[PDB]
Image: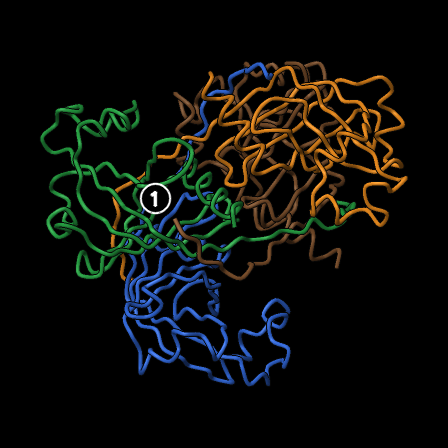
Chain colours: A green, B blue, C brown, D orange
């Protein structure tokens, strides 16, 4: 079970996107948001966001959510269960800042409309797609 | 946009996998299921499954679901809104049957464990995420 | 069936597009990604829009033997494509293959003097299927 | 540029397949082979293969080769330049051996037909696919 955790975190780290939907918000639509973590593994999972986000209004102390994740190549799928809440911690913003994130905010870090979500993931259900290479056939074309 | 729909249906047909969860079932977890459609576009969206699928007991006459879909390469994300119910129609099993589906059922089409779900999708929110190639950089390897 | 393979490969190439094409004696033989285009659902030749200043263009002469490396998104198909590569900037062909994505790369559009078009007439490919089967899902502490 | 190396080595480690060709062999066809490295970064790059592989007859003391590489999701393309030679080192077989390697040998680690290649890559030309995420649009369907 060590390897499964590893594959998931590596995939999440490089591919990033998580489709995050909340039942009573935005009709339950699973919005693609680019995840970020500190280091190569372990939660929490962070999301840069705008104070005006409708999920921002309705998370409060915490909300149970399911995030849908797939690796770009579709060789892994993860259903991520956890609590999502706003945590616009300025130290966190410093740790996670980069030119890509930077582009989204006219204000830069100080931008009043910048928000940060954290997802505390306690568990995920994970599906590996296993592929078998078959013998290559020469075909005239 | 008709391009958006066309792209969505194209990607769904070739890439197939949709992650599907139900509130109040298995903590809401979204399961990867492979989608099938008759023709090259237009719902409903069908999923072959097993009668002992947890979701089946809770569908009743049809429940609202959100399907999470991404294309391979992730150049398209779709959140598909619609209604999901078991419609294990023999006519439908026959129209959609293929060697890949066959592999899963020991009993063939007659398999007592075979179930079929349909998703009637009234709408999808679609995000394009298309890639553009940067210039190649030469890099020394250690 | 050998018919299955050709069909899957043409489908993958049509949708995935990218082929990494290298040439001996050019740029150390490195294989650059270039996006393939074919008229219709299947069958060559394979067209590559490119720039006139491509050094690759300089070295083609009447046509050259090239090996193209292809993989499908998700890596369920690999193809090594053997064929002759030469420039064929046919104005009629430019129109048949033109689109906004192609258009974006050229200042003058079709009018651009730097616009070049390469054709790959492929006699044969080696094709590897690498299909995937989904494993049962495990739940992990996190 | 450090980032590029990290991305490449990450992609290589998780995705593995390199399509490798040699001029004068198999008409120059690039056969997909699964790359292995010790650790998470740095060459050499190892390939398990067959003693009867036509490639082995032609490698001699070593040959310059180009390997075509893409990540499964096609967000990274790499043309790898290096020297390729057989180095069926027994220690190396133990070090890189695994259930997936194990699937190919009727005789296992001690299969007489087992052969190991090493690619000593000095450099690679690397292309990144930059994705741009548009605003979500609802469609009727």
- Which residue is at 48% across, 63% downward? B34
Q: Relative to B63, say whether D81 is above or below.
A: above
Horizontal side of residue B118 vs A89, given as left or right: right
Horizontal side of residue C129 vs C53, given as left or right: right
- Which residue is at 23% across, 24% downward? A94
Dot 1: chain letter: B
Rendered location of residue C117, percent (x, y): 56, 27
Total labels drawn = 1
Q: Relative to C130, say whether A101 is above or below.
A: above
Horizontal side of residue B122 vs C36, given as left or right: left
Q: Relative to A90, say whether B55 is above or below.
A: below
Which quarter of the figure has residue A86?
top left
Rendered location of residue A73, percent (x, y): 51, 45
Residue ID for mark 1: B128
Q: Quadrant of the N terminus of chain C?
A: bottom right
Between B49 and B70, the one nearer to me in the picture: B49
Horizontal side of residue A22 vs D27, given as left or right: left
Rendered location of residue C86, percent (x, y): 67, 25
Q: Relative to B110, say whether B127 is above or below.
A: above
Q: Secondary structure at mark 1?
A: strand
Rendered location of residue B49, percent (x, y): 49, 73
Pointer 1: residues within 10 angstroms few (<14), some, or many (20+)?
many
């Amino acid at each position: 079970t060590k390897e499964l955790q590893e594959k998931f975190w590596k995939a999440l780290k490089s591919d990033r996107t998580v489709m995050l939907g909340l039942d009573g918000v935005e009709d339950g639509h699973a919005r693609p948001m680019t995840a970020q973590i500190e280091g190569d593994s372990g939660g929490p999972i962070w999301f840069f966001t705008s104070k005006d986000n409708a999920l921002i209004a309705m998370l409060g102390q915490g909300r149970r959510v399911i995030g849908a994740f797939s690796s770009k190549g579709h060789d892994l799928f993860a259903s991520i269960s956890g609590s999502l809440r706003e945590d616009t911690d300025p130290a966190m913003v410093d740790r996670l800042w980069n030119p890509y994130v930077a582009a989204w905010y006219e204000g830069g870090k100080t931008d009043p409309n910048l928000a940060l979500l954290r997802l505390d993931a306690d568990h995920a259900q994970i599906w590996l797609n296993e592929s078998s290479l078959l013998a290559g056939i020469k075909v005239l074309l």
